[PDB]
Length: 141
Length: 139
Image: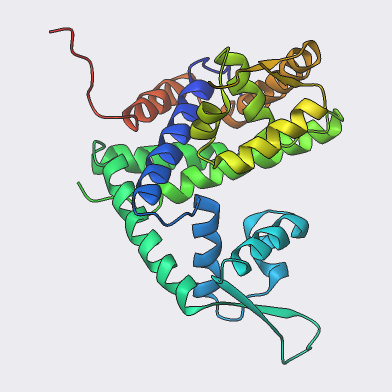
């Protein structure tokens, strides 16, 4: 618990803003009509076939009400589909339509490209130092 | 230079932590706002005369979604509109915004407090590094 440097909050926020700006710009130029949260959601559904709406919201630290609307949005765009769960058949399983999987694979490709561009100016040690300091802030909360 | 696999996840984790803390704090102070609202109010305050299209660009969200958010903030008497329409905070908007601002700095202070003064200064340098490549050119 030491005094807080005044430049930190503004500096952190400028990085967050620069990242979403650059990502959005590359997403829009490939005309995917997706935002980072959408890409995030498709990625989680693909990596866990049969993912549950409840588990989706939990993994993302978001109220179910929010997650349901986003899913509703993606379903309305034919990127996501829901099907009654066979097991306890009281839940609903999430799956990517063929279009959703395709758009997810392309969005991810541009994501890793933007990531490389954003952190390239940083040496391997500078990056690891950045990860470590960020990690220490969180671990002490 | 290879890209560290844990860097974006670390940044996203910090983003998530800040968002949930701000939300929680806003709920405790009963300001009836979400983190995105705070962000919107901050951009309008710091860029006087901002129009719907610019706000949309900075939020990285489409005009349709941004239009709805502003209509809600107008109905709540926090924002007012005035070839393009400029956005201004109302007196209530300025005050609510100032509340959010205090909550914002408190959340960031708790996040950074555990770091030593040297770790903080170093964090700032690394963060400055993550910003757009070498620009400056006066000649």
